[PDB]
Image (cartoon, helix red, strand yellow):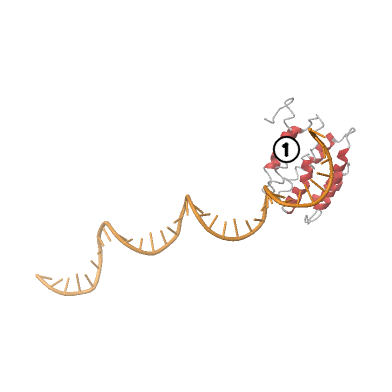
Amino acid sequence: GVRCSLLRLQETLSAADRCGAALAGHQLIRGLGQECVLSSSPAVLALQTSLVFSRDFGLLVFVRKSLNSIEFRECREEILKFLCIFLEKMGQKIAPYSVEIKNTCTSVYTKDRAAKCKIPALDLLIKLLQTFRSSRLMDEFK
DNA sequence: GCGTGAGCTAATCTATGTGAGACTGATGTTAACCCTAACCC
């Protein structure tokens, strides 16, 4: 929600001693998402994807940027719990940048060796919740 | 007829450990083939 999301939470995965500040990241991601209750012109639908999912400073890419971070692979799991249930808003017909987010979720599936009921079974509800609300563009999913 | 919130107990769920089944390769053992102390015709 707040534009300062990059400044506040991209700093977290830059410093050493990743043991700790995972709860700080959890507080940041709860604050950015408590604002999701508003429904009058959010104007952040196209903003989040370029910020939380982009290959440059996204958060789903913070699995390829989390592989070496074993201490930040279960903490990453715990923050991405809420980061992946963030999609829980079935009141929009918008489908921007869903094509690449599909394979991003596929990568999230084929990345984590553990938390198999915590990172998976938490992803791939984009399928059957977000996707298959489709067959209007349907370029690559099937 | 039916929503909606609280507490609970059932159901996980991964980390770690242990054993059963399949497998693989180094090894030593038995064995085919031949040579050798020694004598003595």
**Left or right for A11, reference A123:** right
Residue A85 showing in the rendered view: yes
* Residue A11 pos. (x, y %): 83, 49
Q: Which residue is mark 1?
A: A125
Question: Nearest the camera: A95 or A132?
Answer: A132
**Residue at 78%, 41% in the rendered image:** A85
Amino acid type at mark 1: Leu
Return the residue nearer the eye: B6 or A73.
Answer: B6
Res A11 visible: no
Q: Residue furthest right?
A: A40
Q: Nearer the viewer, residue A3 or A93?
A: A93
Q: Position of residue A12 (x, y in %)?
A: 82, 50
What is the secondary structure assignment of the residue under circle 1? loop
Quadrant of res A41: top right
Disc 1 residue crowd, few under 14, some 14–19, many 20+, Cα 10 Å:
some
Q: Is residue B24 above or below residue A128?
A: below
On screen, residue B36 versus residue A133, left or right, reads left
Q: Percent position (x, y) of residue A56? A: 78, 41
- Quadrant in which residue A38 is drawn: top right
Q: Residue B23 location in percent, x, y?
A: 47, 50
Q: Chain of mark 1?
A: A
Quadrant position of the N terminus of chain A in the picture: top right
Please state the total of marks drawn on the protein image.
1
Q: Residue at x 71, y 35 (%)?
A: A127
Can you say which quadrant of the picture contains the C terminus of chain A? top right
Q: Is residue B14 above or below residue A52?
A: below
Kindly identify the residue that appears in the image at 82 percent across and 40 percent down. Answer: A51
